[PDB]
Image (cartoon, rainbow over the protein chains, first blue to last red):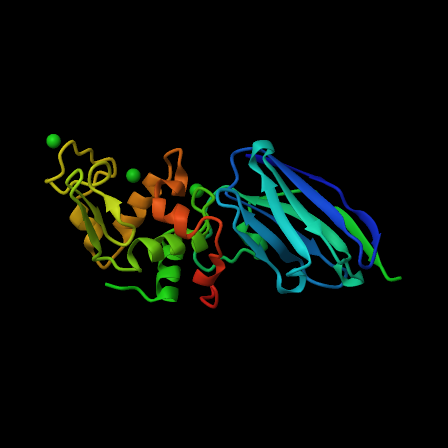
Length: 127
Length: 130
Ligand SMILES: [Cl-]
Ligand SMILES: [Cl-]
Ligand SMILES: [Cl-]
């Protein structure tokens, strides 16, 4: 299968930044993503990136502030989180696919992913 | 047949192209756009080796499909090229999937390298709900 290992995370003040990384081992991935579970909200796709062509998707709420990228040499994906706001506070989870999206399955749907990281805490506080 | 943009997006999605070997639906769309303008009947003859490119992905008859008139032809997709000229693109999708299992992946197509790679391709799927 595919073992996912998350790194990064922590506490930061609004306007600041954090870089999350996720490394895959095992089967080769077709798609890697970050999901997040904010307090008092339902879980949610944050950004996704296709392993083969590097095409990225972003949730509306992080567009222009977050950047997802990768280094296939190291089977490693990165989420650069800039201009962080309190509402970005959440558990962030790495996710991966080893195949295509089924019809009706969108990049932001947790059901579309078969492999998950253990979750990384990110806490943003006001100034 | 000439597909409409979102019509084609949904169709390729249904045929399992979105994320196939890590290639996004957006890039497959850009490929179809810049190979044939989404036209299943498209053909391009290459007087240089007497081969022909067929269908929505402009798959070439020397290596990939059999058109019975290309010298030194291999039929790696094991398909009649005529199969790549049909309104239903199931066979074309399977052959395109085969192409990209080669080391180049989607870079096999020089139009993709020049018209898609390094360029905006989000425009091809925007608003389609795929
Ligand atoms: Cl695949
Ligand atoms: Cl021959
Ligand atoms: Cl095949």
